Amino acid sequence: MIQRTPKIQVYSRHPAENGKSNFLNCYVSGFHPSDIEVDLLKNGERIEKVEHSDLSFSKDWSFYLLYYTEFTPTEKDEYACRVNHVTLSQPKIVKWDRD
Image (cartoon, rainbow, N blue to C red; front, side, top):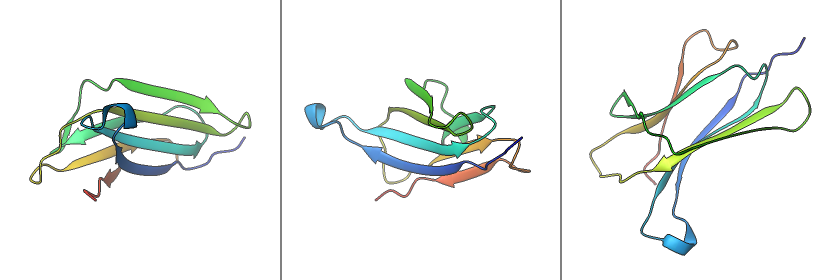
């Protein structure tokens, strides 16, 4: 057996073809086993509608998830990604840096 803790990165992107749109991304990488729970949070509340959840693997024991959806951030709201995985004794919450 092998188990590897996910790396978690939270960032925003504007698609170049529609630059007014903005997407909140949580990229969860290099994890094993593949069992996982991932949410985007707005002010601590789970965002129920997440448009995209793309899972892949490289080696048979290395998984990658890109979990992202359109959002409209204001200066006051706080966004984050929350991950649960067998390697994490507590849920890991990674806050989005606004810049």
